[PDB]
Length: 235
Image (cartoon, rainbow, N blue to C red; front, side, top):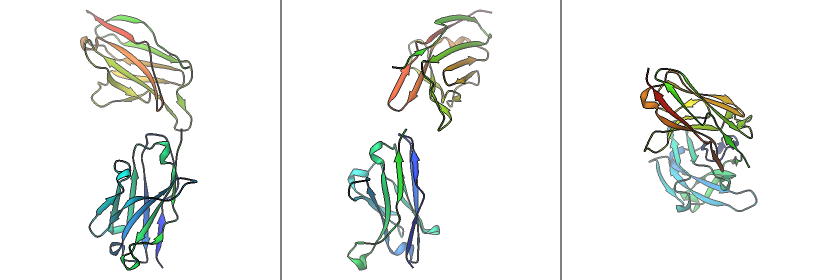
């Protein structure tokens, strides 16, 4: 009668975050707390913490504070766990288990477990070295990597474009080669794929005086392009 059904297996990229489920049945969901145990492949069992459906209160194993986040939903008799900033050491099987007072606080029934697998020199050259352009003209900058920054898996290009104005800290303009950060004028448009990328400024303005850097960005490895200095001329 009692059953703990956990969500499917997850294959994720480092630094990512997952959130698994556990749907209870055959017992008053709020009458018993819900625990979460981690089991790294060959190794033993490790307690993460629990959630008390009745009052959404939770206790954590100190070690998982900042990693695991328990939570519940009385309406669907479901407990959730959310792993954040996934590292390789987060690859393991995660179980949800119901704790019972009438059972010496031991874990009555267990979920089947959810599998979480966290799994995945170079030259960045970009020109022109610099260029002066008349206010209003369209600007075009190039960036090329010795090896493709395209991930066929995720189907994304791991390239970013930073803008650095005189005496200021670099600012992020575009990521994933073509996504514009919030607060970045529509003028700026990143494009390209694999090896060759290009940052384009629709109609340059006086304020665009800066040096633009492209960077291949993937966890574990970051490479900055030589940068392109841009100055604005009158007209």
